[PDB]
Structures are given as structure tokens and as C-alpha cells.
Amino acid sequence: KVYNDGYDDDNYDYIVKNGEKWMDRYEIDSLIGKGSFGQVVKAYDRVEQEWVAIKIIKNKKAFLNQAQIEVRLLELMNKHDTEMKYYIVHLKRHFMFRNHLCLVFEMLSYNLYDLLRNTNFRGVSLNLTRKFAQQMCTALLFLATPELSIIHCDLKPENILLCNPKRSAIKIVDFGSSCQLGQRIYQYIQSRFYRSPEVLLGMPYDLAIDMWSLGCILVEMHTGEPLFSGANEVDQMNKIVEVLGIPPAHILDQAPKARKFFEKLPDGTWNLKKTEYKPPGTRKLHNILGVETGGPGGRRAGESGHTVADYLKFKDLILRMLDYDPKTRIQPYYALQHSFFK
Ligand SMILES: CC(=O)Nc1nc2ccc([N+](=O)[O-])cc2s1
Image (cartoon, rainbow, N blue to C red):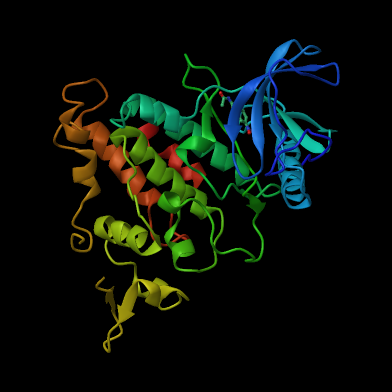
């Protein structure tokens, strides 16, 4: 009939009410986000005299233990920042309130998926995409810090918010799915579109999987559409094969889940499995990006920054970001050296 003295609901979520005041400090405005973890709300802090975003975690050990891992990581990252010149969202403070662990974050603006939606999925300019791509490469450079060595493990356009709606400065949010580089515990990781080949193949993974995710995201910010929109793991892998060809033999000879998508003929070479799809590596990125045809669907014809020479620099970086082999996939540091950022 009632859960937690009438504060909680069926699904262990605090019933957020408008105009409620918590701890004589936070004035609740309205619900803004939702997910597995629980809820997210817009709140005004009377002390610091500023808007904040409070992540109200579900009243259940499982979710509370996950949140406590996130806090550990956010405080670990925020300890190595202070200046906030590395594009990780700032965990201000946390506390328990009516049996919910709350995480007070700075109030960020709408996310990149919201930005995509506002273009009717026609995408944004290369000049703005560069800016995002530069900040993210720096963000990943930060996470690659030896003492951190953090894998976000769930990069997508919804986990990339703007600081201000009239600026291009961004922040990465949601480190609930993240864990520091460790021995392989979990295998079904990342959102499907942005899921690396090594994960799909069930091989050892590291911080490179975040790079793959960025590659996929950056193309999508410009074209306006997901690069690899798989309806399931098999489809997802086949959309990748369309663009980049068949993964190298030496990868697939190691892959535990190789046979889920491919088949090893008597010669010792791999081909697809018939279930549809263009042949291996014939839906070229050059053509998707529209290097020599005025960009995605010709919509960027004769705009500054969108020349053949610009697009070619963009294309090259992305191909290095989408390198099948994670040992060779471009590292954050050298991505920033790339001529796309001159
Ligand atoms: C949705 C909106 O208008 N503003 C939001 N800002 C932030 C900032 C941080 C987090 N977070 O969970 O780390 C979520 C949100 S939602």
C-alpha cells in the first residue's frame, strides 16, 4: 500500500514533488532525467545560490551500491581536476535523504541527442563537430591518466551535455556503467550502436572501446544519423562490416564469439554468415561523409570549413578512431595532434 512512509513508489523511486524543500537547503523544481539508477531533478541550492541537478538514486541496495561506485570515480576524477579543464561533469557533494543517496551535480544544459533531434537528425556543422571532437579527445586523454585509467564504457549522444545553451562547451555525464581498467568481469557492455568490435567479439577490452564510441558519435553529429544503427548484435556487426570490411584474420582467430557473425572456411579465412547488406567495405565513409559531394546529402555545399581538404582530414581521423585493432586504434594524445584540429 505504502513504500517508505509514502515517499517511494512501485519501482523504488522517490515521488518527486514540485516546490518541496530538502534539508532546509534544496528547493525542488521539476523532474528532468530518468534511468535505471533512479531519477534526476532540477533543484536550487539556497546556500551556494545556484541551480543544481540532483541524481536521486533508487531505494534499493543494488542501485545504491552502483551509485557508490560512481561517487568513488567522480571524486577520484574531480580530485585530479579542480580547475575543471578536462570536461568531466562535477560532483559537488552527496548525502542521504529519506533513504535515497542523492548526488548533487552542476546544472548542465540539454544533451547532444536533444541537439540532433532539433536538427531533425540532419546534423551539425564540421566546425561545431570539431569543437566537440576536440573536447572529447581531451576528456579521454584525462581518463587515460595512469592513476585514473577509467573507461566510461557507455558513451552516447545522450551522455554528452552542453554547459550552456549558447556555447559549445560540453561535459560527459553518467559514470554508473564505468569501471577502471581491470580484469574482464562483464561482457555485454556499452550501448549497441557505439559498441566496439572487441566487445561484440567477446575479446579483452580496455580504454580503446571509448575511442570507438567517439568515432561513431562524431560521424553521427555531422550526418545527423547513427553510423551503425544495428537492431541487434548480428545486424550491428553487419553494418560495421559494410563500411570497414571484414575484421583481420588474427583478430577473428582469437575471438570467442567469432562464429556468431562469421565462418572459418577450410583455407583459414573468414567470411560473413548469410541470414540484406552491401558487400564488405563498399559503403565507404568517404561517401557517407560526402567528401566530394557537399557533405551529408549535399546540405553543406559551399559553406566555410566544409571543403574537400577539410572533409578529408575529418575522414582520416575517424578511420583511425574506427581501427578494428585496439592496439593500433589512435590514442587520445595523438588524436589531438591530428591536422583536423589546426
Ligand atoms: C537534463 C537537464 O536539463 N540538465 C541536466 N544536467 C545534468 C547534469 C548532470 C547530470 N548527471 O546525472 O551527471 C544530469 C544532468 S541533467
